[PDB]
Each structure stands twice: as structure tokens, then as C-alpha cells.
Image 1: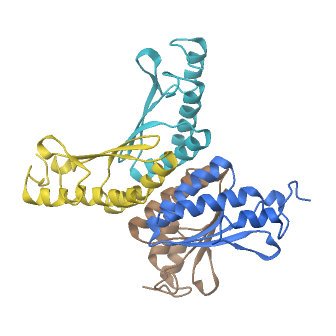
Image 2 (image 1 turned 60 degrees about the vertical axis):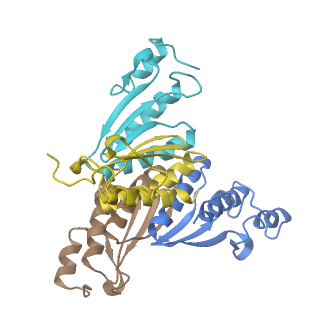
Image 3 (image 1 turned 90 degrees about the vertical axis):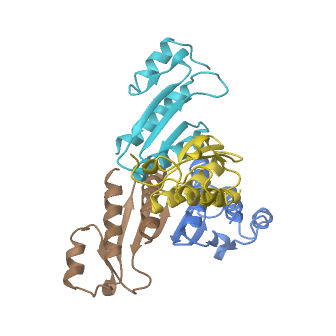
Length: 102
Length: 98
Length: 98
Length: 102
């Protein structure tokens, strides 16, 4: 009984959004998106995570992320929708842009 | 130097960080930290990040909003070292503030 | 809306953040925070950074190791607004943890 | 009575180090170096400061920095030397590299 509408698997809109973040992979049932970000070291990884943290608390939409030294393993979905919303793709896009710097 | 499962030093170190859970084979220690919100969790993580890069010893941590799910082990040792307990302790102290 | 020097609202807000010092013309409020070390100061600043970008209201802060010398004012207002006192309060609360 | 030796003003070594960080400016008496870093927004500035913070606590050598939204105004010197040392230029260089990303 998720209070929010999720983007339906393979919906034209979902796919139009995915196209903007092509290095993320859609998960089974299209219920989330995943990307493992790789940096040279922890210092770079934290620099990246820092910008995402600011964005996340500003839009109040947070990554499920697993950091191990130079690696940041990320899965995005909207809990209140039990799946993907526009906020996940907007978060993925910001993350992609912040990582592009490295 | 790798700490053997149930070794005297491991058990002694573990007493300094009693909220941590020894894992199968004593290959790692785990603690899940919980805060009021992400802002608090990030303030916590920020202090740990600084410590981690200073001593060059890094957590395996999974953050979701207000929680930080942490597993510590020495990657080059295939088990626990002193550095893991030292990090666990720094993390405990940083968490106390909240 | 810009708070006029010595206005009733300014003085009332100032009571919620008594460690802050009103500046000449009541154009800003200042507080210098002190911590044990940089690690603590950075943990403090990190929480404030998150708050600041959330509400889109930023401190004028000068950090040297363990100290954070802070002046707050609303750049578009040429003086103090509610947002400055709200930020001052968030900063006070973040500092309390240390 | 500074416990540490500072690099003498105009010393060949000072100048050889300054050459590596050409956008920093030497201060009167060559007692410090200064650079005002400019970013697009606070989010970028904090991303930058974050990496420098990690470096600073690792080498235990900290900037005197004044952040105002998208701007980071920095002055580096070694207090225990009452002037510049190699650590200031190594810090400036790291800062330059972290900022280059933006």
C-alpha cells in the first residue's frame, strides 16, 4: 500500500529518464536503479559523496549507498512508492554530474 | 598483524568496543549506528571520514538516511587487526555526541 | 524582510541565540565557535553545510584548525533576517554536541 | 622565537615551490600565500573544501580559509615557522588539484 505512484516498468517516461543516466542499471521489475561509482582513492570518493549529501538533504531524497575506500555502490528507489520516481533519476543525474569531475 | 579468532588480544580489544558484534570466523566487526536524521548521520560520517584518511584505514559502511551500517576489517590481512578496533573506538566516540 | 536595528522581533530572536553578538548597525550577528581539534570543527561545519544548502542560506565563516569564526547576514537584505537567526540556532544546536 | 625554519623571502626553493602553484600570490615578506577559489555554488565549494579537509587532517596542516557561498578565500602559512614551509606549498598544490575538477 505505497502512498506514492511509482513509474511503471518499461513506461515511456521511465525509459526517457533512464536515457539521461545511461550508466545506471535498471533492476528487476524496474523497482530501482544501480550504479557503482569508482574513484582513485577515498579522498576523491568522499569529495563526491559530500556533494551528493548536500543535494540529498536539500531535495530530501537519499541514496542507499555502500562506500568501501574508493568505491561507492549506489541503489536508488523511492520507498513511499515501492519503486522508482522522478526523484530517483534526478538524484542519479546529480550524482553522475558530481562524479564526472573526477 | 592479523588477530586470530578468540585470541586474547582480540577479546581484550573487543571489550573496549562492546556495541560491536564479532562476525563469523571473527573476520570482521559490525555495528549499525542510528541517528535522528541524515544531517546527524552525515555529521557523524564526516568525522569518521577524516579519521579514516588520516590513519589510512577505511570502514565498509552502508548509509541509508539516518542509519550507518558498518563492518570493519583489514583488507590486506583477511581478518581483524588493531586498526579495526581503533577505528571502531573512534566511531563509538563520534557517535556518543548524538 | 530586513530586521531593523533594535526592532522588537530582532531582540526577541536574539534571545534564542544569546551567545551571538549583534554587530554595528545590527547588520549581522557573530559567534566564534571553538572545538578540541579540526576533526570536531569539521564535523560541526559538515552539519551546518547540509542545513545551509537545504534552506539556501549560508554562513560567512572563517575556519582555522579548531575554531570557526562566523558572521551571519542576508546578502540580499543588507542586514539581518529571520533566516540568520534560524541558522544561528541550528549552529548552536550542532555545537552543543561537542 | 619560531621553533621551525621558514623559507626565506625570495629563496630559490620558495620560488621553485611557488612556480608549482602559480595562481597563489605571495604576501608581503613572503610570509604566506593566498588564493581566492571561486566555484559555481556552495555545493561545489563544499565538495572542494571536503577533499581539502581530509588532506589537511591527514598531513596535519590546515588552511586559514574564509568561505562565503561559492567562494573560498585561503591564506596558507606555518605558524610554528612564522612564515612559509614546504607544507604550505604541498597544501596549496593539493587544493589547486581538487579545484581543477570544477
